[PDB]
Length: 16
Length: 10
Length: 232
Length: 272
Ligand SMILES: Cc1oc(-c2ccccc2)nc1CCOc1ccc(C[C@H](Nc2ccccc2C(=O)c2ccccc2)C(=O)O)cc1
Ligand SMILES: CC1=C(/C=C/C(C)=C\C=C\C(C)=C\C(=O)O)C(C)(C)CCC1
Image (cartoon, rainbow over all chains, first blue to last red; front, side, top):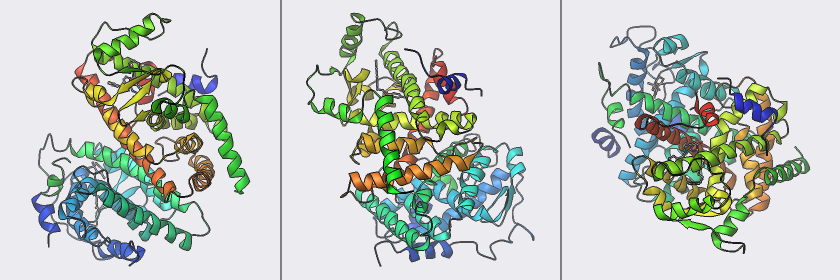
């Protein structure tokens, strides 16, 4: 599964 | 729906 | 009596069990048939319970007062969820398995072997264990099933609004029953209504399977279940 | 919980909701009704109007990923996909603002988002729709329901289910403050497949439900059984999601160059 980006989104968020 | 229709009308 | 008496709903549930006796036909002595496949034993029970569901429905206040064709529509639209809710609640009595109305006990690993695990696991965790943890009684199960029955979105209804009104009468009787029987837990009403989303997705997933255990056949199923499977 | 705590939760969710979502229901309805002076939406009712709506961006700043090159269905397919991907990011941020959420096992956080995101996208998509169409591109455009229903093969029936749902959902007349709580209630669903620690999630959801219950009684005093009618929509949402998934699967089978954005592939992989 991993869910790489979901993880990233929770971790930091998103750029401008 | 033979069965269902039949069972419902008694 | 009061639009949607909770007592008659309970009586409808009790009236069409199990509840002793019906739990011996094929679990400790004999057992007509002899099918070698858990999915078969399950489809048979379902087919059998379809007949009892008709009787159950007639006992739910105001169902029988709906136009006959509407009754047909409602039962065709909700039979899988109505039956899943029944066997799931009945299964609260057992650990890691399901109790069929035919008195047959289907264990987890058999389902996993038959290739229908996962869906079977969702039933156990999302429905059975949820029903067990909150210990929903038969009155509650009955009302939730009545809510499933009275689905206004069923295509073809002659008067959707009437069905919605009936469903709403059940919401009111259930909430009233919960506050009187469970004043210690203000949010039981909501917890109950929130058992419906899982029932719907599992019901949908189950239908997807049935439509696969048909479009391949090989030793068909039973009439009625097959009739219900001709799609809404 | 004491009413004050529930009222604080509700205000806290409302504020973070305004911070997470640019186009609120209040604004959307204002645009849809014709009561906010500040250019009005470009109406897309057919293929020519869809082109003069996108090529209108050509003169703007090249940001809309992909442009024409392949039929009119792929154009809509990329517009929804883009909006969806943005929505997941906005929803993810809003979820982190729910008290107790970031304190949950990371894995459960991911699972709640995995399963809650589309249910939320469709709940909010309703805010931008009325019987005749839906707002798009931050409300700069309005795409008609008929037009969407007229797309080819399976593309033509993707939105129809969402409008039917929207019409029934909008009849409850919920406003942004009611929605902020409802959405949080959807996220904190303790019945998601694969959850590791259920109790924490259910405990938080119980507080959110009490807060939503009080909000509806206070904000909608004459509407009977609104709380019950609202929770019922959560089961409706499961069906819109699965039915949409099945429709995406038809596209996958019927077109070799499906190509779905990675985040959406991530979410749909082993879902329900
Ligand atoms: C209806 C509409 O159109 C535009 C738009 C069109 C052209 C240019 C710019 C915008 N904005 C909106 C409103 C947002 O309406 C939305 C509708 C659905 C979703 C869920 C999202 N869908 C997709 C994810 C990837 C690829 C396709 C889709 C699809 O839903 C789809 C739609 C029609 C045909 C085939 C597929 C999912 O994750 O499953 C999000 C927003
Ligand atoms: C559970 C289950 C399935 C379907 C069940 C349905 C549609 C109804 C069951 C009713 C029962 C089991 C009633 C009773 O005995 O009272 C399918 C075959 C898709 C796959 C394996 C798990």
